[PDB]
Amino acid sequence: QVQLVESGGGVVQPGRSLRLSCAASGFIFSRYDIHWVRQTPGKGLEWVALIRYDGSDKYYADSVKGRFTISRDNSKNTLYLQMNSLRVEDTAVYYCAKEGIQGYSGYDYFWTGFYFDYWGQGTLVTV
Amino acid sequence: VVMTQSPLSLPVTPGEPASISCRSSQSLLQSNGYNYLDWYLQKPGQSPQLLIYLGSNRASGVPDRFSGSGSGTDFTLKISRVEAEDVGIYYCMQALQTPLTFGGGTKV
Amino acid sequence: NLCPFDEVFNATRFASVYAWNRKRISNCVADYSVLYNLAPFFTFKCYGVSPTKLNDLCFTNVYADSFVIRGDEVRQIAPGQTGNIADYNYKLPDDFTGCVIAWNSNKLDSKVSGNYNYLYRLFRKSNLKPFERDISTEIYQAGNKPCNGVAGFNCYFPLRSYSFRPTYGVGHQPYRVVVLSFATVCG
Ligand SMILES: *[C@@H]1O[C@H](CO)[C@@H](O[C@@H]2O[C@H](CO)[C@@H](O)[C@H](O)[C@H]2NC(C)=O)[C@H](O)[C@H]1NC(C)=O
Image (cartoon, rainbow over all chains, first blue to last red; front, side, top):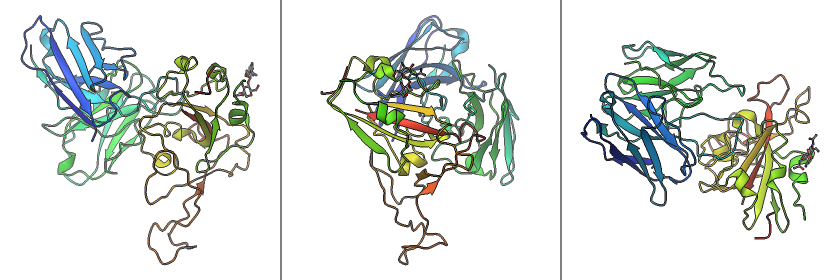
């Protein structure tokens, strides 16, 4: 019943931005992460960015590291990602992917790694 | 880190088993004895679904024929029984640290 | 008042999985900062409330239901997990609000002939409601009725043991977890 449904993407224009939102439910969407991964056709999936379950701290891919902005939205179980200043080679469907370890705030010896148990459906965005 | 799979295309007639391998730039096996590559499949026209995680133990809801072997750098997915349901490109995320250099991608 | 954790962490005898002793602690002043020192590599996975933030915060009651399980199952006792311990032995409610301390304990948990004082229920007809404890030793007809109060083709005896020895891998190395599950107590 874990559900990640997303909308907002579409045809856009190079140079401007867009707002991607991946609404979640079925699970307690305040406990554990959501990642973003994109695959442009003719290329394997490229990881985009994550967020730790309350917006504790963020990382972004080395290919972006700042022109991309992700922001959680608790209290209504929705996620928001805001792109800025798209390039030519960014037309790619964006998957919001839930990762199946229910996030902890400490420091474990056994990590179990990032793994995106349940996914979304993608939003084709084209520059 | 960069992941390179093999073979990016293993058209496997049904039944006999097919193996898919990935390479790592660094030894993913961390001092706790866990490997971290993740195999993600996706049938054509569908979202990717988790197939293995942490290299060895698969996600609940995945048949037994998707066994995956582990190493220090050379990991492998074994598809014992290939049929129609198994078609789709695979991937090997390295799950050790940001960024997750999501692997190249094979075919079926 | 100096809340007693000297028992649940430093007690000599070590509880097994199914008989996890939920030692309720209360009406006293605790200090969670004391704990971050032992396990050179602890686990402190605080589901629910930030480890450092916890010290100047508190709730009604605390339950440090310590026991011992295999190292590779340290990852297993986390809320929302679906493993062997999770389904049949010990589970955490999805809205868990505690800290899961877990450390390697090679010594005093490893005889050269093996310490087999630990068992784990590998079989059960149905999964556990959050925080259920079951000492029931009765014989598991994983397979047919007949009468089952002893059998041996396969009925099965739902409470195996483990094997703990220094030469084992770290995953096989036994670990003692201390799961804390949470206004008379805070420091
Ligand atoms: C369990 O016992 C050990 C043995 O003393 C405790 O480790 C000491 O903890 C005190 C503070 O509680 C420190 O001042 C000492 O430096 C520690 N010992 C060493 C060798 O560094 C441990 O704290 C005890 N744990 C509990 C929960 O009581």
